[PDB]
Length: 158
Ligand SMILES: CC1(C)Nc2nc(N)[nH]c(=O)c2N=C1C(=O)NCC(=O)NCCS(=O)(=O)C[C@H]1O[C@@H](n2cnc3c(N)ncnc32)[C@H](O)[C@@H]1O
Image (tube, rainbow, N blue to C red; front, side, top):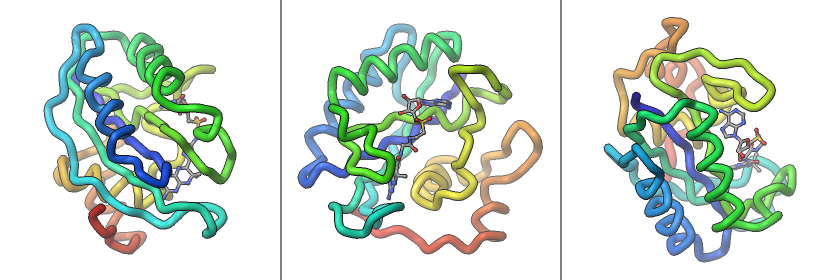
């Protein structure tokens, strides 16, 4: 299965954190990274007076079940980040969000796939569009169409 995962951090110097996370993603059992997007420097969604976030998207090949994948991404978040990643409008030490999981639709207590707000977040959509410009969601929506419809500002690279 190809899972698409969003990475964000707004540590002041986030490259080492983001690399640690990427390495951890690759080390997940029965999984490996297919592709990584460029790293983007994005203005905070929330209070403007925190550092900018580094956002990226990753394609991960996996034979884990979706909730097993989430178990790992949450583990990585605990091991690599702190309860900065939990302040509601930031800062965020490290978030890992499962955007898509194959062509599955998931709505459980633990998981909402496709991700619950990605269609409102250019910082999730643009890096995804870099690595998967032809992406079609399970319901038939097209990533390209969402970006065209909403006109979200293009992102600057880190
Ligand atoms: C502060 C805010 C909004 N602003 C940002 N501005 C910029 N430029 N860039 C950012 O990356 C950025 N991130 C933000 C932010 O808060 N991001 C994380 C976030 O939304 N957290 C609240 C939602 S959450 O389900 O708890 C996220 C958390 O739920 C878990 N999770 C992962 N995938 C999931 C899924 N598909 N369904 C359900 N849970 C999943 C995981 O622990 C994740 O951190």
